[PDB]
Image (cartoon, coloured by chain):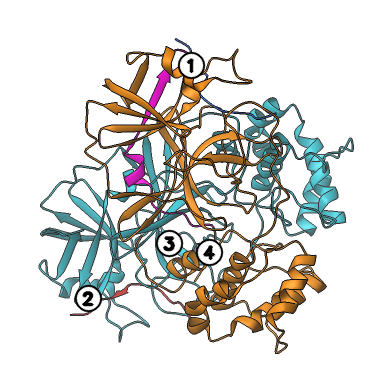
Chain colours: A orange, B cyan, C red, D blue
Amino acid sequence: SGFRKMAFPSGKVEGCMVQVTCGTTTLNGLWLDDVVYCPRHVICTSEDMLNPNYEDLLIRKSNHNFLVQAGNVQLRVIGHSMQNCVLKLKVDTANPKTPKYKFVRIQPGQTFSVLACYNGSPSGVYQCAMRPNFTIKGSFLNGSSGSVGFNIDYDCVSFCYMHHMELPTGVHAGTDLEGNFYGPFVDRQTAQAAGTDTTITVNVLAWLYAAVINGDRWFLNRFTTTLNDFNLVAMKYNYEPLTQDHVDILGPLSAQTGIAVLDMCASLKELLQNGMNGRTILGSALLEDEFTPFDVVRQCSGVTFQ
Amino acid sequence: SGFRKMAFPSGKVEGCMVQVTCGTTTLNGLWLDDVVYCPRHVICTSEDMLNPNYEDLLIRKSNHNFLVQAGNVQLRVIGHSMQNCVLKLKVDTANPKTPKYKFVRIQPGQTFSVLACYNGSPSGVYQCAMRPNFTIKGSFLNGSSGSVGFNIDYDCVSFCYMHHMELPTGVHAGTDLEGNFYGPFVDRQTAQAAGTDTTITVNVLAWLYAAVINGDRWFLNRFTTTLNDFNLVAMKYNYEPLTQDHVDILGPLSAQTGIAVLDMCASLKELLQNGMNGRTILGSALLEDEFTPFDVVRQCSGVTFQ
Amino acid sequence: SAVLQSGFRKM
Amino acid sequence: SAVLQSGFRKM
């Protein structure tokens, strides 16, 4: 049994990151084969933090200005290039620990295990959910840029994130390994605020599925409501609307637990209307919403490895 | 900023575990140097579940009956022995990835990152807190025995747990690598129930420190109460009593945030008496209590690596 | 009763 | 204001 914030193993990602330094500005970089993917903040002094000119700054920097350290190993930068909003530093050494990697741009709501790092030493790993406003509620400090988020399935790693900045409201922002940001953010110290945060409904449904399977079934009731009424109530309660695709992806959980999707949709609607009533579901008094159905399946009674 | 359930990196522990099999009963084991520490559940058929005779069972099993698999690598069992409630299988191959390991028996309330595993493949890693009733609220299923919990400091790993059983109330139990249980349990399918669960006060205070430093300071107030009154209120609210040592270990956080210990003790007492009043502290509507002050220091503004 | 775990491996 | 991050290493 048991159910809590469980993150993927990190060794395959622990052994594939280095420290990238330019002058007095350093950060973490994701090392794959003979390439190092790093945020382009590396070529930025403190005085030009407001409106960096990344083209001019990159065309000013040289090959030897980039310093790559894999623990205590020194790496030479054979070449450097920029794509979108990241830098690929072609290095002379191929990483022996690089696993089967994919660069996927995950849609909002899909969770992933970020590897919080500082100066090339993995500080830790924890789950995060890509919010609909295209931010992550991670725990990062100065020097944590380049802390990649990833998924692991069938012993294959898919990197889907690279941390870049904190928003003033406390949430964090990042790119994919291709370079494009997640959202309308810009790579400069300009006043940027994410949109209104909306709680993900499908993740809540997966969390309720996990609660039912674990042994907590007080919220279940015989009452059943249609999809459209549930969508209206979620909209007036600031939750993401539920589509047919979300019900379709919940099919394995419905088969595993034996409760139909609409039944727990009605139960969830009633939970919103009457509140949580003061009691507790699996150690949380608020609806946890960073649990995808795939994560529930691979973490609950299913015995999926990685 | 940011603050959530952050667990230690696992690669140094991912690369040091194998699968131990006897007949039709398999499970996970911790491989260190030329030794494999496994639960003695491995020598257990389904029929003798009530009162296993581990001495007779071990004296009946032979060396070749134990099968050790490191992924796709087959390991020969040179010898086997029992200590307390674990088996050390001396194998012919020394693990090249074994790090500096220590076997520490953590006191209740000290958190640790369990590496949930299934059939030798690391399924994931997540934080857990050793409850005062000497249980952990982990997420484990069948075949997860041997999933070691560990801490990492100064790139040195200290194993402090090994999962063995689930209690009927839903919490899990385990040993240390020395073999002694954490609590009054017995290693058999006998009806065993843990005592009344008590929330750890020092961990709550550390969580409040993290909330204050992160930027949430609504609960703070000028009211201040003595230690004895706070202890009485915690006792009548089913929390662990607070001693002088707990205030002493909280010193670094007091210096970092500038808030006196008794001030937040009074604030916490008032929170207990008046409830949480429906608002939220860092995504949780209940007092999180699996955050040690050391974990807060190494996770918050402190830039400690591993 | 305890649900003390180990894997149920075939063969 | 954005808190665009990197390391604050000296030398």
Residue wearing tag 4: A292
Name the disc covering residue B174, or none. 3
The alpha-carbon separation of the residues under discs 4 and 3 comes to: 29 Å
Q: Give the SS element for disc 3.
A: strand
Name the disc covering residue B56, or none. 2
| Residue A9 inside the magenta-drawn segment | yes
Task: Nearest to the eye among marks 1 and 4: give it.
Answer: 1
| Residue B106 inside the magenta-drawn segment | no
Task: Nearest to the eye among marks 3 and 1: give it.
Answer: 1
Q: Residue drawn at (74%, 75%), measured in percent from left and top?
A: A269
Most extreme residue toward the bottom, as rendered? A222
Given the image, on which type of amino acid does mark 1 rest? Asp
- The answer to whether tags 3 and 1 share a subunit is no
Return the residue nearer the eye: A247 or B107.
Answer: A247
- The answer to whether tags 4 and 3 share a subunit is no
- The range drawn in magenta is A5-25
| Residue A273 sits above or below residue A62 on the image | below
